[PDB]
Amino acid sequence: MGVAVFLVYQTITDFRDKLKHPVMSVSYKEVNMYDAPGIALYPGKARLLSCEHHWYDHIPPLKDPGQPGENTCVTQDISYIDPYTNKTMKHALIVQGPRDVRRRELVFLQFHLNETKQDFSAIDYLLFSSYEAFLKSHDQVKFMQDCESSFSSWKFSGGFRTWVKMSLVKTKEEDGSQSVEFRQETSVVNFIDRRETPDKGDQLFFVVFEWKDPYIQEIQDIITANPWSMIALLCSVFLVLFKAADFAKLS
Amino acid sequence: MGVAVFLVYQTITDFRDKLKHPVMSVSYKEVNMYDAPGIALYPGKARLLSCEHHWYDHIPPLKDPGQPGENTCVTQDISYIDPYTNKTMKHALIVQGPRDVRRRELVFLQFHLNETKQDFSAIDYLLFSSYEAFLKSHDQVKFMQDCESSFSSWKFSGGFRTWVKMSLVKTKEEDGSQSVEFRQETSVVNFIDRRETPDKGDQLFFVVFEWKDPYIQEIQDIITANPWSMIALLCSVFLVLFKAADFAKLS
Amino acid sequence: MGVAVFLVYQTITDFRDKLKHPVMSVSYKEVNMYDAPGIALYPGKARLLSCEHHWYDHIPPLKDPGQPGENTCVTQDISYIDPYTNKTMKHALIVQGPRDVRRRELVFLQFHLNETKQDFSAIDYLLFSSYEAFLKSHDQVKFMQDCESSFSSWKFSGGFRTWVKMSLVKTKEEDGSQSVEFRQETSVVNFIDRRETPDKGDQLFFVVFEWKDPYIQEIQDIITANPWSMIALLCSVFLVLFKAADFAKLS
């Protein structure tokens, strides 16, 4: 009897320990064509020059800095308002990201910034999951607000390329909903300004966005214990101790 | 009987496999106000100019390059000794970290040094868990030594800002103790020299420390199996096979 | 009877849910001496100047750039062919990595590149597991193609140092094989050109490779459920329900 009560006490405490915190598992999934995200860039003073997509070409052809044109980009720019303060004005320009990963597709963005007083020049940017959901559905102006309140924005360095290789992670929370977040790693490459005339000193920006790997990481949180197993086990131990008592009575 | 012995062999092998290596789980938690950490710096010859804390103001006001002043930073500088070799004398400068996470308080630092024969510009730094533990408690001079031998130090570049976003990860080892480590990612933004445009070419540094997200990740290693469940299951299989043998005898 | 059928329904559904996706666990391991790995380089037109190993010296001695010599490096330079397109010929350079981890040996490389038409100067590089596997075993010319179609190559910026701290992550899949992949984070330090100050403006590169920590992270995917436990549990529940039926008959 004392053995039974100690066993049931330890079992119930173990079940409490198991239920108070779950376990986490990871998984991967391959996509034939990535859903094209949207990269949000705050031009601010800066003016775009050329947004180009390189679907399969290994090398970007040699360019001529300082001139606009060659805009083959799906762009949508509307002035907005920051919901974090609601009294400040934020302005953005939205583009469509790289689609196919099998053939490396990189979007190449040239940015020229006019002369400014600020010592450290950089342009902020932000990424959200998909572009078509922001383009067509209703009430997406507030979608930008909640996306920026949820997603995080990190500015890229102003002066040289920041080759951005992004990735997608889908965590499956158990309350009937899904969460998507973007993980990216950047690679800065110094640029030679000798070809351009740097006597003016006006900063020129360059950004390249790419898909790191076709696979997307899926993370699931698993509950490790169920009441049915414990109740069956304790019933079995009760039965076996009853059988032992019956044997002792037979003795 | 043979079924019983094979089942017990398989179960004991499974239990040994479960016991030899555990399974990890992750957890998060919110904090109202982060504990003020400490940032350890090794300026060398680079005497600093201005350490300022920006509780909510988004942007540091433009800083005149070179001229000192505006020290609103809790700092202390004491010459130390390296425990790794014990014959090399190294000096460190210690500051307190940012605290306000909801207002994302950031610390702004600056450095200046006359040109030397180092051929490069970089200042090493190191982070430990808290400042009040280094200040008030007894025998913290050796706390520097064992924290340095435990923590890892990475130098920041010299000539442009290195925006550091740090987060604290707490892993709960099972032997009645706890471990704290810092995970950080840096962001470098180029700095324009044309403002001062001097002929001396003296290096100027800029560092910004910040908290990434309020969430603290907790990692615990959980053992997947316990002997009580396995012993109860083997007792149950013994009982059911005994009942089958009794039924066969009745037959 | 209905209780039994619903319980087995829930049990079989839970077992299917456990079977479809397993759980993942992580582990660490110390090594007395890391195996010497191999670093792949694609200099192209940039003939290197000096490859040096700093077995224990914390500090690299002051150098005089612009002139070749002092090649104390285990190098193997060959011309290859890209299997991705199979009509492109690319040249590679192969060196051995650092070995000593307790003394944290670091490898120093200097590259000089003549002025090029490309507006952004960078040298791509790739990492594979070991050097003696490429050098001594048979048909490793195709091992280069295998590794470059398997491993990922990331270019380093040209003009300033890119201090690379690599680490080895060894995951072991369940179908009788293991996977080794390298995770690295770079640390760029600005390089001062005031020492030479030429009017040619030719590029100079510097790379330093070093092990991050002696620990090797090992990842195993663990199956969480096995048929023996659930079949024994359902047999036990069937037996106890049969006992309940016998008791009801007795009543």
Image (cartoon, coloured by chain):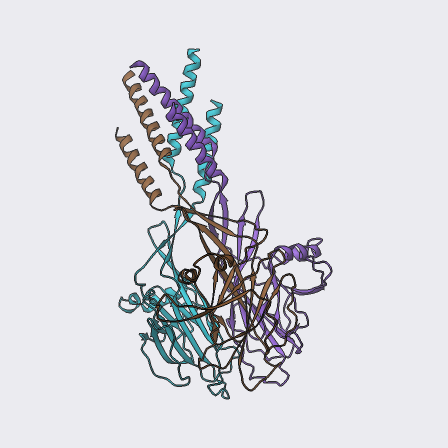
Chain colours: A cyan, B purple, C brown
Q: Is residue B132 visible?
A: no
| The quadrant where residue A135 appears | bottom left
Q: Is residue A249 left or right of residue C195?
A: left
Image location of residue C135, percent across then percent down: 50, 60
Image location of residue C24, percent across then percent down: 43, 47
| The quadrant where residue A209 appears | bottom left
Q: Is residue B201 left or right of residue A197?
A: right
- Seen as rendered, the residue at the extreme front is C138
Image location of residue B16, percent across then percent down: 48, 36
Q: Is residue C214 visible?
A: yes
Decide which of C227, B34 is in the foreground and name it.
C227
Does residue A113 lie above or below A149 as drawn? below
Decide which of B73, C120 is in the foreground and name it.
C120
- Seen as rendered, the residue at the extreme top is A251
> Residue at (35%, 18%) from the top-left corner?
B245
The quadrant of the image that shows the C terminus of chain B is top left
Does residue A119 lie above or below C134 as drawn? below
| The quadrant where residue A184 appears | bottom left
The quadrant of the image that shows the N terminus of chain B is top left
Image location of residue B143, percent across then percent down: 67, 55
Does residue B216 lie above or below A63 as drawn? above
**Number of marks drawn:** 0
Decide which of C138, A86 is in the foreground and name it.
C138
